[PDB]
C-alpha cells in the first residue's frame, strides 16, 4: 500500500484537477517513474502527514512560547521528551519535503526527485525549515558543557523553533486551495479565519514577549512584572496578565496597569501596539469583505434599479410613470438580479432543455396545436417562448392591430374584450392570440390584463423558424 | 375564523410569492388537508404570534439578565408570575412550531403535520427551544426542596432562558425576508439595524456578566465591585457602572476604574474585549457597505467617465479634445449612468410605448408628414428616433453630404446656413433634414448647432423599415 | 431688479437643468405668475440668502452652545443683541421659506404660493423651524417676570436654537446637489466633508454637554468639573478640557482624568461614547469609499487581467505562453481599462470623426490610394481602421496566405521577408499589404514584426463597404 | 556623456511611453534643441538625482526634527556641516528643477527652458521649495548677531526645512507612476506603503512636537516632561517616551502617563489625536482595498454563481435541478470567472492561433478527415470548435435526431449505445458524430456521457463556413 498512498488516488479533487480517471491513472504512473522516494503533492500521505504536522505545529507554537517564557527549567525530563519528539517529527518532515513533488503555477507537479524537488527546496525554504527543525538550544547546551547568561541564550535560541510558523502558513495555504477545488468554501470566510488564527497566535506570542524581555533582564525594577509585584506569582497569573496586557495593546484598549516606565517596556509596548493595530485594521478589512459578499445579490439588484431611476430622472418621467415602472420591476424580477440569456447560454443543451421544460411544458402541452406534436418539436417551441409580465389595465393585445405574437398565460387573470360577446376572463394556464399563427392578418379581440399577468409569448416569426426545421408538423 | 387565520390570506406578499389568487387559493386548500393543526409560515397567525413573541423575547432578554444578576431574590411573587407567564407563552410557541409549515429553499412550505414538520423541528432546534422554554431553575428548586450554593446554581440555570435569542434571531430573519418581498427595504439598512440590536443586547449581557461573575463568587476582595466599593450600591449604580465597564471594553475605550486585578476579572474583561472588538469591526464593515450603497449611482458614473479619460489618455488626445469630450459627457448623460437599450428591453411593450410617447410624441406630432399618420404608425416611428446631443459649433448636417438621417430638435438653438438665404435659426421643437426621406440624394443646407442641441434623429433606413410594416402610409 | 433676483437667471446650472434659454425664459415667466411672493429654488436670491444663512447658522451653532454652557450671564446686552439679531435673520428665513418654490422629485418646482408651498412647509419642517427661530428663552423670561431654577430652564430652552442644524443640513444638501450639476465634485470628497463638519459640530456639542449637565446640577461633588477642581477656571480651560474629554470619548481614546464616578457622568460619557463610535465607524466607512474611488481605473484593469490569468489557468496554458499574453496586455492596453466600441458609440458623429482623424489621419494620408480621395471618403475609411499590436517575432502577414486585410504601421519596426529581395525593414508610418485590396488573391511576401508593432488594419471587406457608399472613388 | 544622461535613453519605460526607438530618438533630439540646460523628466539623471534626493530627504526629515527638539545646541560644528551640506544638495535641486521638463497631462513634456519650465515652477512650487532649501535659521542668526528668545525662534525657523516633505511626496509620486509603466505594481500595495511611510513620518514628527512645545516654553511645571520628571533624561528616554506618547494618541490607545493638565498639552494632544485618527481611518480604508483586490477573481465567481442561484430561485427550480446546475458550474468553470469570447477578441491573430492550437490541435489531429488537411485549414476549423461539458447520464447525441454537430472528446468516458452492437465506450481523445458532416440526415447512434465529459463540438454550419473559404479541401 506504500506505493498507493504516495500516489494521487482517484478522488473528487483528483478527477476535477486532472481531468478523469485515465488522466489520474496517467499521473499515478508518472509518480511510479521514481521509486519509494516521490510523494505527490496531492497524495493522501501528503494529506495525512500535513494533518499530523498542522496539529503538531499549532500545539508547538502554543506550548513552546509558554514553556520558555513562564517556566524556569526547560531541561527537565518532560520538556526534553516533548522538544525531542516534536523536533523528530519536524525533521522527518524536512526529509519528506525533499522527496515531495511541488505544485507549479502554469505547470505540472515538479516530480523528478534528484534535482526538480531537492534543488528547489534548498534554494527556497530549506534554511528556515532547518533552523526550526534542529534543536539549536540543545546543541548549544551540549557544546558549552556564568550559567545564567547560558540560560538566557538558550531561551532566545529555543524561539528559533517558532519559525515552524512558515510551515503552518505554507501547509494551510496548500490544503485550503485543495479544499477550494474539493468544496466551494467562500473565500471571505476562509480568509477571515486565517487572520483570526494569526491574530490569536500573535496575541499569544506578544503576551509571552512581554514577560520574556523582562525575564531575560532579571526582572528589572521598572518592569511591569516587578511594578505590579507579579515576579513570584503562578504561571497562570503571570501568563493571564501578560496576555491581558498584549491583547489590550492589540485591540488598542489601554494597558495592564500603567503606561510603560522602562525603555524595554516602552519599545516592546510599541512593537505590540504596531503589530496589534495592523492586525485589527486587517480584521476590519476582512470583516468589510465578508459583509459585502454576503449581500452581493441584493446589493447588485439595488444598483440595477438605481440605474432605472437615473434613466427615469434624465427623461424627467412623471411620478405616476415612475411608480408604474417600479411596480413592473418588483413584479418582473421579484428582487432578483440575473441574466437569463447569459445564464442559459452557459448551460449545456440537456440542462437548458430541462429548465425550459420545467418552466414551460405544462402550459404549452394544454394548447391543442402543440398537444399532438413530436416531443422534439415541442422542445424547440418551448425554447422560443419569451417571459413577459403585463401590469393591471395593460392591453396585451389590441383589436385591429397586426398579430405578430401569441400568448400563453402562466399566471394572472386577463380578460378578452370583444364586440360580439365582450366577456371572457382567461385565468392561469389559458392561451390567447392563437389564430395569429398562420393567418398573418389582424387580431379580432383585445385582451386586457386584469391583474399582473405573467405570460409566455411565442412570436409568429419564431414559430415559423422552429416549423422550418421540422417540415411535417 | 380559526381556519382563515391559519391560512395564507390574499395579500400583496401572498400574491407576489404565490402567483395570484387562484395560486393563493390553491395553497389555502393545501393547508385545509390537515385539520386545526397546520399553520402556514406566511399565515397571519404566524405573523401575529411572531409579533407577540418578538416583543416578549426582547423584554425577557433585557429584564431576565438584570433580574438574576442585580436582584438577590428571584423567588419573590412578582418575579415568579413574570417568569411563569413568559415561560407559558414560550412553551405554547414550542407546541405551535411543531404544527407550523416551514418555508423550504427550492420548494414549497413543508406542511404535512405528522412527519414533515414534527420530525424536522426535533432534528433541528427542538432542544435549544426546549431548554429556553422550560423553567429549569424552578424544577431544580422544587427537586432540591448549603442554600447559598443552591442560589448560585439557580442563577446560572436561569440564564438558559437566554437561549430565546435563537428564536428572536430566527423570527426576525423570517419576517425580514417576508418584508423584503412586501417592501423594498435596503439590504444595508436592514443588516446594520440587526447588528445595532445585537450589539446593544451583547453590551447589556456583558454588563450583567461583569457583575454576575463577581456576585457568584461572593464579591471577592479583588473584584471591581469590592475595589470600587459598589457591593452595597443601588441596582441602578451597580448596573450603570457594569454597562459602562462593558460598553468601554466593547468600543474599546478603556476601563471602569482600573485594569483588572483578579483572574475572573482579567478573563471576563478579555471575553468582553474580544466580543466587543469583533462587534465593532462588523459595525465598521456594515457602515462601509451602507455608505457605498447610498452613492452607488454617482460612483458608477465616475467609474464610467474615468474609463473615457483612460481611452483619451491611451490615444494621447490633445487637452482641447479632452475638454470637448468632458463637456459632451456632462451635457449628454447629465451625471447619470443608465443603459437605455437594456432598461428599455426589460420593460414590456406598453411601458416602452408610454416612455417613448412622453419623450418623443410632442416633437414628432408637429412634423406635417407624421401629423396625419395613424397613431399605430407614429408609435412605430417614435421607437426609431435616437437621442443625439450636438455641442456648440458642431455641424449636425453638412451641405453636399448624402442625407441618411433627419433630425427633430428637442432643445437648443441650431442654425441653417445655406447659399441662397443663409440665415435661419431653428429653436426648440423645430425639425430639419426632412427632405432626406424619399429623395435619397444630397443635402442642400448645412445646419450648425449654436448651443448645445439635443435632437432626435430618425435614419432613412429606420423610416423605411416602419414604413414597410404599414404599406398605406 | 427684485423680479430678476427672484427669477432663475440664465446660468450654466439653469441651462443644464432646464434645457436652454427658451426653457429658462419659460420658467422665469412661470415665476412671474405670482407677484413679489415667489422665489425660485434655483434663484440667486435663494443662493444669496442660503449663503448668508449658512455662515450665520455655523456661527450660531458654534457660539450658542458655548454661550449657554460656559458663560453664567446670557441676559447681558451683547448676548441679547446677538441672539435677537440672529433670531430676526432666522425668522425672516421662515417667512421666505413659505414663499420659495420647492424642487420636487419627478416634477417641476412647486411654485403656487397659496397652497403648493405654504401647505407643504406647514406639513413638513415648519415646527422644527418655528421652535429654532423663536426666542423661547426670552419669551419664558418675560412671562415669568427661585431664580436659579429659572436660570437652569432658560439654559435648556435656549438649546432649542440648535434645531437650526435642520436648516444647515437641508440647505447644504440642496446647494451641494446644485453644485454637482454645476461642477463635477467627486461624491466621496463631498460626503466625507459633510461628515467631517458633522463630526466637528457633534464633538463641540458633546464638549459643551459634558459641562452643561454638571453646571445645571450646581457642580455636584462627584462631577469631573469639581473632581479636577475646574469649577472656577477660565472659560478657555473649562472649554478646552470639556472638548478634550468629548473628543477622547469620540475617537474612543480614554478619559479626561478618570473614569466617571457619578451617574450623570456615567450616562453622559456613554452617550458621547455611542455618538463618537458611530461617527468614527462612519468616517472609516467614508474613508474606505474615497480610497476605493481614487484608484478605480487601476483596480478595474487588475480585475480585467486577473480574469485573463483565470482563462490561462483553466486551459492550463504553458508558462511561456502566459508571459507572451502578459506582454501583449502590457503593450496593447498599457495599464488602461477602456471599451473603445462603447466609448466611441456614446460620442456624437463630429466627436467620433475628430478622435479618428487625430489617431489615424497622418498614416492614411501617406498611402497613395487615399492621398487623392475626397475627405468624406477618407473619413469613412479611417473609421474602418482597427488597432492591432503584434509582438516581436509575430508574423503579421504570411506568404501564400489569402490576403483579407492591409496594414498601416503606426509604430514599431517590421520587416518584409520575401524570396527575391528578402530584405526590407518598414518603420513608423509605412504601409504593407496594400496589393490585397482589389486582387482577391494570395500574399507574395511575409511581414514579421521585429519589435512590438502597433498597426492599423483595414479589412478588404470594410474597404469594399466604404467604397460601395462612394461609387466614383 | 552629459548630453546622454540628460536625454531619455532607450529603456523598457521609454519604448513603452514613446512608441519605439524612432520615437525615443525623436524626443532625444527635441531635448538637444536647448543646450546643457534641459533635463528630460524621464532622464536617468532625473532618475539618479531623484534617488539621491529621496535618500537625503528621508534622512533630513528623520534627523532634523530630532536635532532641533532633543538637542540644545544646533550651532555645533557637526550640525552646521550636516545642515549646510543638505541645504546645498537641496538648493542645487531647486536650480535643476528650473531646467527639468515637466510631464504634462494631455501633452508632451514641457521642455522650453526659458518660459515653459522656469515660469511654471515659479507659479507652482518655487516658494515652498525656496523656503525649505534656504537655511533661514542661519540667516536670522547672522543678521541678529535675550539670546534664549533667539534660540527659541531659531528652533521654529529650522522646521521650515520640513517643507521638503513637498519634494519627497512629489518625487515619490513621479517615480511611482514611471515604475507602474515599467512594472505592474499592484496599486493597493503601492498606496498602502505610501501611507505606512506617511504614518511613520507623522508619528515621528508628533513625538518631536510633544517635546518641542514644552521645550519652547522652558518646560512649564504642568508639562508632561516636568510631571514625569524627564526634563534631565537622555535624548533616548525623552524621544522614546515622546514617540510612545504620540503613537499612543495616533493608534488612539491612551496616554504616556496621565491625561494632559496644561493647555499647550491639551491642544497638542488633540492635534495628535485628530491627525492620528484620520491616518488610522485611512489605514483601515487602504487595508480594506488591498484585501478586496487580493481575492477579486474568487469574489467575482461567487457573484456570478449567486446570480445563477437567483435565476433558479425566480423560476423555483426543484432542489434536484439546482444541484445538477451547481455540479455543472463546478465542472465547467472550475471556480474560474473569465469571458472566453472577450479575452480571445482582445488577443491578436497569432496569440489566438497559439492558444487554440495548444487547447485543440492534439484532438483534431487524430481525426482522419483533418489529419491530411493543410495546416491553414486545420487552424480555421480549430477556431470553430466550441467547448462543452456534459454531466454523467446526459445524452450528448440522441438516436434519430437530426445531426447538426460533431463532438471531439477531450476528457471523460462516454458510451455509444446503439441497436446493433449496443456496447462501445469512447474515452479521452475519441471523436463521435463524425458522419454528421456531409450527409445532412439523422444520427444512427445515441452517445450518453458516463462521467463528466469535456468535449469540443464543431457544428456542421461552422464546418461548411471554413470549408467555403478553402475550396479544394
Ligand atoms: C527602496 O528604495 C529604492 C527603490 C529603488 C531602488 C533603490 C532603492 O533604494 C534607495 C533601485 C532603483 O534605482 N530602481 C530600480 C532599478 C531597476 N531599473 C530597471 C529601473 C530604473 C533604471 C532606470 C533608467 C531609466 O531611465 C531611462 C528609467 O526611466 C526613467 C527607469 C530606471 C528603483 C527602485
Ligand atoms: C462555511 C463555508 C462558507 C465554508 C468556509 C470554510 C471555513 C469555515 C474553513 C475552511 C478551512 C478552515 C481553516 C483551516 C485551518 C485553520 C488554521 C487554524 O490554525 C485556525 C483555523 C483555520 C484558519 C480554519 C478555520 C475555518 C476554515 C477557514
Ligand atoms: C428605510 C428603508 C431603506 C427600509 C429599511 C427598513 C429598516 C429601517 C427596518 C426593517 C426591519 C427593521 C428591524 C426589525 C426588527 C428589529 C429587531 C429589534 O430587536 C431591533 C430593531 C430591528 C433590527 C429593526 C430595525 C429597523 C429595520 C431594520
Ligand atoms: C475637490 C473636488 C473633487 C471637488 C469636491 C468638492 C468639495 C471639496 C466641497 C464641495 C462642497 C463643500 C462643502 C460645502 C459646505 C460645507 C459645510 C460646512 O459646515 C463644512 C464644510 C462643507 C462640508 C464643505 C466641504 C468641502 C466641500 C465638500
Ligand atoms: C509587490 C508588488 C505587488 C509590487 C508593489 C510595489 C511596492 C511593494 C513598492 C513600489 C514602490 C515602493 C515605495 C517607494 C518609496 C517609498 C517611500 C518611502 O519613504 C517609504 C517606502 C515607499 C512607500 C516604498 C514602499 C514599497 C513600494 C510601494
Image (cartoon, coloured by chain):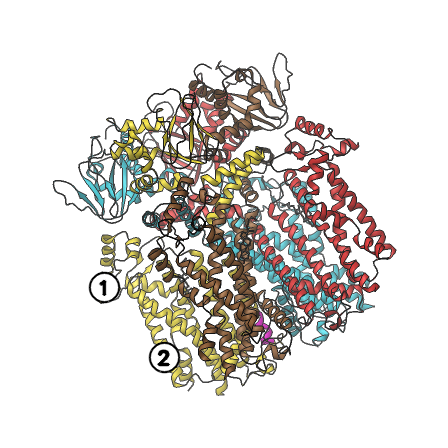
Chain colours: A yellow, B brown, C red, D cyan
Q: Which mark is residue B305?
A: none
Residue C224 seen in the figure = yes
B352 with respect to C229 (left or right): left
Residue A247 seen in the figure = no
Residue tagged 2:
A84
Q: Using a 10 Å C-alpha cutoff, classify the residue at mark 2 as few (fewer than 14 neighbours), some (14 to 19) or many (20 or more).
A: some
The answer to whether residue D216 is above or below residue D181 is: below
Q: Is mark 1 within 8 Å of ligand 2?
A: no
The answer to whether residue A94 is above or below residue D302 is: below
Instruction: Chain letter for mark 1, please.
Output: A
- Image quarter (top left, top right, bottom left or bottom right) of the C terminus of chain A: top left
Element carrying mark 2: helix
Residue C465 is one of the magenta-drawn residues? no
> What residue range appears in magenta?
A263-270
Whichever of callouts 2 and 1 sits on the residue coming sooner in the sequence is 1
The answer to whether residue C213 is above or below residue C1 is: below
Dominant secondary structure (helix, strand or loop) of the stretch shown in magenta: helix
Element carrying mark 1: helix
Determine if marks 2 and 1 fall on one subunit.
Answer: yes
Looking at the rendering, which quadrant does residue C447 occupy? Answer: top left
Q: Residue furthest top?
A: B420
Q: How many marks?
A: 2
Looking at the rendering, which quadrant does residue D195 occupy? Answer: bottom right
C398 with respect to B455 (left or right): left
Q: Which mark is residue A4?
A: 1
Looking at the rendering, which quadrant does residue D422 occupy? Answer: top left
D43 with respect to D126 (left or right): left
Between B367 and D133, the one lying in front of the other is B367
Residue A268 is one of the magenta-drawn residues? yes
Cα separation between marks 2 and 1? 31 Å
Q: Residue B460's x, y, as percent?
A: 48, 20
Amino acid at each position: 500500500q506504500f506505493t498507493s498512498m504516495l500516489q494521487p488516488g482517484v478522488n473528487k479533487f483528483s478527477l476535477r484537477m486532472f481531468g478523469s480517471q485515465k488522466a489520474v491513472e496517467k499521473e499515478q504512473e508518472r509518480v511510479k517513474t521514481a521509486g519509494f522516494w516521490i510523494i505527490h503533492p496531492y497524495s493522501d500521505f501528503r494529506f495525512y502527514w500535513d494533518l499530523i504536522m498542522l496539529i503538531m505545529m499549532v500545539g508547538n507554537l502554543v506550548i513552546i512560547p509558554v514553556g520558555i517564557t513562564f517556566f524556569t527549567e526547560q531541561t527537565t525530563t518532560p520538556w526534553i521528551i516533548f522538544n525531542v519528539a516534536s523536533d523528530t517529527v519536524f525533521l522527518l518532515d524536512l526529509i519528506m519535503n525533499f522527496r515531495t513533488g511541488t505544485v507549479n503555477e502554469d505547470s505540472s507537479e515538479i516530480i523528478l526527485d534528484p534535482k526538480v524537488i531537492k534543488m528547489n527546496y534548498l534554494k527556497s525554504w530549506f534554511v528556515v525549515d532547518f533552523i526550526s527543525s534542529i534543536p539549536v538550544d540543545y546543541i548549544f547546551l551540549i557544546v558549552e558543557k556564568r550559567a545564567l547568561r547560558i540560560v538566557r541564550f538558550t531561551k532566545i535560541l529555543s524561539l528559533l523553533r517558532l519559525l515552524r510558523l512558515s510551515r503552518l502558513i505554507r501547509y494551510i495555504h496548500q490544503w485550503e486551495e485543495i479544499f477550494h477545488m474539493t468544496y466551494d468554501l467562500a473565500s471571505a470566510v476562509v480568509r477571515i479565519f486565517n487572520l483570526i488564527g494569526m491574530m490569536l497566535l500573535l496575541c499569544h506570542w506578544d503576551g509571552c514577549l512581554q514577560f520574556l524581555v523582562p525575564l531575560l533582564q532579571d526582572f528589572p525594577p521598572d518592569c511591569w512584572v516587578s511594578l505590579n509585584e507579579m515576579v513570584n506569582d503562578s504561571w497562570g497569573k503571570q501568563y493571564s496578565y501578560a496576555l491581558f496586557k498584549a491583547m489590550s495593546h492589540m485591540l488598542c484598549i489601554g494597558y495592564g496597569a500603567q503606561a510603560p516606565v522602562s525603555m524595554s517596556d516602552l519599545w516592546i509596548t510599541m512593537l505590540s501596539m504596531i503589530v496589534g493595530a495592523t492586525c485589527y485594521a486587517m480584521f476590519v478589512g476582512h470583516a468589510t469583505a465578508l459583509i459585502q459578499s454576503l449581500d452581493s445579490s441584493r446589493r447588485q439588484y439595488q444598483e440595477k434599479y438605481k440605474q432605472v431611476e437615473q434613466y427615469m430622472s434624465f427623461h424627467k418621467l412623471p411620478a405616476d410613470m415612475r411608480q408604474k415602472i417600479h411596480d413592473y420591476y418588483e413584479h418582473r424580477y421579484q428582487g432578483k438580479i440575473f441574466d437569463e440569456e447569459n445564464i442559459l447560454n452557459e448551460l449545456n443543451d440537456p440542462l437548458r432543455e430541462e429548465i425550459v421544460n420545467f418552466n414551460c411544458r405544462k402550459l404549452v402541452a394544454t394548447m391543442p396545436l402543440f398537444a399532438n406534436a413530436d416531443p422534439n418539436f415541442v422542445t424547440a417551441m418551448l425554447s422560443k417562448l419569451r417571459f413577459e409580465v403585463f401590469q393591471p389595465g395593460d392591453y396585451i393585445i389590441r383589436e385591429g392591430a397586426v398579430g405578430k405574437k401569441m400568448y400563453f398565460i402562466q399566471h394572472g387573470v386577463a380578460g378578452v374584450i370583444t364586440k360580439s360577446s365582450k366577456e371572457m376572463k382567461l385565468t392561469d394556464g389559458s392561451y390567447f392570440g392563437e389564430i395569429c399563427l398562420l393567418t398573418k392578418g389582424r387580431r379580432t379581440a383585445s385582451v386586457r390584463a386584469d391583474t399582473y399577468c405573467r405570460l409566455y409569448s411565442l412570436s409568429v416569426d419564431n414559430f415559423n423558424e422552429v416549423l422550418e426545421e421540422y417540415p411535417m408538423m
